[PDB]
Length: 160
Image (cartoon, rainbow, N blue to C red):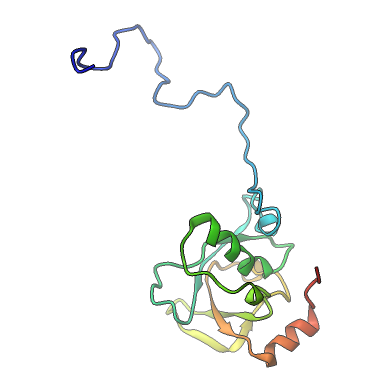
């Protein structure tokens, strides 16, 4: 009650620990339930993963890029795969059609520090690992039937 005034005891305490969390518990981390379905390739447990930033062509807010991690052994497919996780995990950013989930539908394009977009060359994609460049920044480029067939014909998507 307000009558008590103050909420601190004069109990003896040579060493503090109230401010910090007490151990006495195993220190470990667990992957999200949906993370295993998609994030399993996002190197969740791998702290050596590669961070990534995405700048959409329409990115009206270059200050809000996609923040995800990817393994050097998996494929870029994880990049867009997180999109489903991001929608439910943060309940933000308008949703994207699932049928468009297929990484083959969207392509990643390399960009310069100036934010310039290179349409003259594609960026990895389901065809290989993203960290191949070691950079944590990219932009999405249109992958019309022309590019879809090449990437799809090179690395077809697993059914079911």
